[PDB]
Amino acid sequence: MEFQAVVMAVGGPLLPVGNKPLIWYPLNLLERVGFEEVIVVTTKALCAEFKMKMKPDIVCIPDDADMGTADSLRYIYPKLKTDVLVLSCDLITDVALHEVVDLFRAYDASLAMLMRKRDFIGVDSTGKRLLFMANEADLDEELVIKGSILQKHPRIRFHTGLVDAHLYCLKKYIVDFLMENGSITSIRSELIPYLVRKSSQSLDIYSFIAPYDACWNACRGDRWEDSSAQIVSKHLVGVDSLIGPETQIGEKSSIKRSVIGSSCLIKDRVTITNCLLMNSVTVEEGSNIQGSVICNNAVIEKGADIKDCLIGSGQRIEAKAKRVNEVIV
Amino acid sequence: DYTYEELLNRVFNIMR
Amino acid sequence: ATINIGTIGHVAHGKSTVVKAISGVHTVRFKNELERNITIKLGYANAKIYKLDDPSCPRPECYRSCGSSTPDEFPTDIPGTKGNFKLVRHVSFVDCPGHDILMATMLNGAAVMDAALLLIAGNESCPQPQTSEHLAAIEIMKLKHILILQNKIDLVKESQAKEQYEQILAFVQGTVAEGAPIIPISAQLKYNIEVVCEYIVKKIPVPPRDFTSEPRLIVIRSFDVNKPGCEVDDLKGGVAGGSILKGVLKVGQEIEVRPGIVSKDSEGKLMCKPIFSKIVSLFAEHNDLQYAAPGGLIGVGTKIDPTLCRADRMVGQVLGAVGALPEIFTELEISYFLLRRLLGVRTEGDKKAAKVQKLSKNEVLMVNIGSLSTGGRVSAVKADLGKIVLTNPVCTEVGEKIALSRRVEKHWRLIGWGQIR
């Protein structure tokens, strides 16, 4: 048996909706290979938009009001019996995911990580067996290596500048450790109980080599899709963009490094953007754009010149010769 | 008060 | 339980053995983290006071009146005499220390005490690092009986000795201290306790205190002894040494905390089902007086779920009587102002104290409502009106003790306050 997984809601997603919110491809390349009886923990208003998800499996699990991180696992505890995969939301996906789970099978281990595409993390010569990660401020103390763990393992390679993805190929031993030691928390920071060399059931502890997280994560939006579904007007000066169905397709515009959604009033004159706009965006009458992350329910016309000013929801503006300082929109 | 002036008259004859 | 008296001391002079010298009972708990120089809990003692043609301030021990705050030099006074010690007022000392980490402790047990005594340290530098910080949170809760409890000149050198206390009293414009005169003490030498420890009780009368009003209790303790492998019949409620502010708490007295855990379809705030609570057991600091006088502390024993009282996650919950006068809305407004410095560390740069970061959008908030720090994400908040956004439907009475915390590091900061309409 292997037949379950979970994704934690908050890191350590209500307002950010890129084309969709943070759930485009993780369910795709989680479910493009198997995984059709899954258990997702959720948290409210975001728990009831699950028809246009059109996933062949959705099982949501809510929680209490203001919770932490290990308590999620501790409350989904009474029904999970086998191999478990826990994800997070700080992820792009650009890799065939079968390799991390097959190496996690390949040592019969209990742990894993993702460290690929301030920051220090070590692993041996084969690239597989780790010690610990080092960060910018919790390690005000300098760096400590244990004696025997370097006496046996000859070298270690500290890595400099990749990103975490907070994957954990994982199994029942450490979740029993979490339910019995309940007060131990901080799943991102519970690395230190790893104990490669120093047990309630020989051990194997093991690893392998995204978004910017307050809520926005917008700058990584320039990403191809592995648009094509649009009412094709085929007359714009367009490159590196995307749009969905039932969208307004007018004329008189250039385009580069942009994004569009469904049901957005784009019919009158515009210029090039370098700026992403969600669904429900109304633009008209000759708009040159620069540096804007337009969320849902947007409207502007008659001389809008956006220059390095991202937006939000409830956009109410028509004319602003913009300076490059970003503002509330 | 008489206690600050009491200390400066009485107790600081042995104190630094 | 008539009058409380609160010593209030900021960073780095010592508040453990001086609490032992003049108050008697020192504060202790389990996994306590009790002090490093000054404490971080409410330093409370149990007192019964009597004066018998004697200026001294004795304890309920009725034989002598001294302390142990110095090893060498003992000036002492006329202590009193034996004979089944009497009771002038139901008084008891309490403490409120001055780090910035005890916002639960420093904000929950400060509006509920009655008299205040602000202390000046004697183990810090020539600049003043935290003198204008640790009664400025007590500024909005509006205590009245406030005094400068002048503390340390013992190891203090003469260049920084006799004039700089006036500069500290002028540097505390955010602290209500101009109506705080000086009755001095000594943290080491404890000289002449019969006048030094006299008018910290004798000059201080009853505060403006309501006798028979609603007990609108913000609670300070909820503790429990139910370790793995416990007894059988520990059915109790909040096992507390509980300072009350208003309302007489007799036997059979009624008191309600209306939200608790928020009701079904948790987007409303109230359903008409009051919370029935009959507090019989009340420990009057050495005795079981079931009839609790307002203002002073009494050892409170309620009757609720015992599971809910092990780890006190309920610092400052409003328990109010019948006649539910608190408000029902979830859009919290305040009439705030700002902290002018960004102080807590001493320097000569004026650079981290540049400005006051207001509310924003897509940006977090946290503020101790009483002593409850909730928050959430915001939508559109204006410039000079404080619209606190939250997630807890709570029928709290008046959040007139709030501290707008804000992250700059591992520790949060102090940037704001506010008075509820």
Image (cartoon, coloured by chain):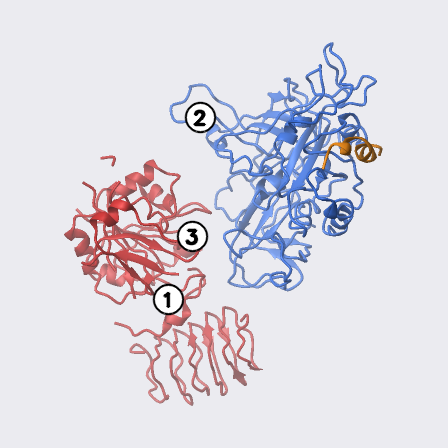
Chain colours: A red, B orange, C blue
| Tag 2 residue | C226
Q: Amino acid at mark 3?
A: Asp
Tell me the SS state at disc 2: loop
Q: Amino acid at mark 2?
A: Asn
Viewer-side label of 2, 3: 3
Residue C72 x, y percent position in the rendering? 66, 27
Residue A89 x, y percent position in the rendering? 35, 59
Q: Quadrant of the N terminus of chain C?
A: top right
Label 3 crowd (10 A; few <14 / some 14-19 / many >=20): few
The label shown at residue A20 is 1
Tell me the SS state at disc 3: loop
Give the chain letter at badge 2: C
Up-down: is B3 above or below A165?
Answer: above
Comparing B11 with A249, the one in front is B11
User: Which is more N-terminal, label 1 or label 3?
Assistant: 1
C280 vs C113, left or right, is: left
| Tag 3 residue | A138
Tell me the SS state at disc 1: loop
Discs 1 and 2 carry the same chain letter: no
Residue drawn at x 25%, y 47% as measured from the top left: A149
